[PDB]
């Protein structure tokens, strides 16, 4: 129902905001050439957010929501970071490179479970999720959707 979607979307948006902590951790580790989950302490679990985790190799962030939001196994959103292949007049986007000093601006793309390709502006597509998200796009903000 439209009303049920409203409840879920509000809570999913809160989860995405709470994941700012992880986006900052990934950026700090990228700036120092460290594994991207290094030093990251996720905030307390809430009634709506079960966990926020960082992939140490790619910097992808997985947000798992509680059953208040979506069923188990259909409850995860993924945020994918990328950088331009070169800062000046890029021709493509590339996944983060573990161990490399990368202090430039990171672009994050949100993927819900039904989003089958990257949809970023110039310089083009970002990487796909490593672990696939499972949250239905209808429950997520529009830029996470197919």
Image (tube, rainbow, N blue to C red):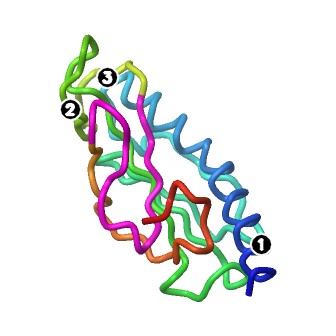
Image-based side of 64 in relation to 128, left or right: right
Specify start and end residues of the magenta stretch as a single range: 106-124
Residue in the foreground of this view, choosing between 20 and 122: 122
Q: Report x, y in % for residue 126.
A: 29, 44
Mark 2 element type: loop
Q: How far, Cα to Cα, is label 2 from label 3?
A: 16 Å
Image-based side of 125 in relation to 3, left or right: left
In the rendered image, the quadrant that contains the N terminus is: bottom right
Answer above or below: position of 43 versus 116: above
Mark 2 and mark 1 lie on one chain; the one further toward the N terminus is 1
Image-based side of 67 in relation to 104, left or right: right
**Disc 1: CA contacts within 10 A as few (<14), some (14-19) or many (>=20):** some
Q: Report x, y in % for residue 49.
A: 67, 67
Q: Report x, y in % for residue 100.
A: 23, 26
Please tell me in which quadrant of the rendered image residue 141 appears: bottom right
Q: How far, Cα to Cα, is label 2 from label 1?
A: 36 Å
Mark 3 element type: loop
Q: Report x, y in % for residue 124.
A: 27, 38
Mark 1 element type: helix
Mark 1 and mark 3 lie on one chain; the one further toward the N terminus is 1
The residue that label 1 is drawn on is 6
Contact between labelled residues 3 and 1, with CB atoms less than 8 Å apart: no
């Amino acid at each position: 129902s439209a009303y049920q979607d409203y409840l879920a979307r509000s809570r999913v948006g809160e989860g995405l905001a709470l994941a700012a902590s992880a986006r900052l951790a990934v950026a700090e580790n990228a700036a120092s050439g460290n594994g991207f989950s290094g030093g990251y302490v996720s905030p307390p679990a809430t009634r709506n957010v079960e966990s926020i985790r960082i992939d140490d190799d790619t910097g992808q962030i997985a947000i798992a929501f509680t059953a208040r939001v979506a069923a188990a196994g259909a409850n995860t959103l993924v945020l994918v970071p990328s950088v331009p292949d070169q800062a000046d007049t890029p021709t493509a986007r590339v996944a983060l490179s573990k161990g490399v000093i990368q202090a430039g601006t990171i672009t994050w793309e949100c993927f819900a479970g039904d989003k089958a390709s990257s949809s970023l502006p110039a310089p083009g597509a970002g990487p796909m999720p490593t672990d696939a998200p499972t949250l239905a796009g209808k429950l997520a903000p529009p830029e996470c959707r197919a």
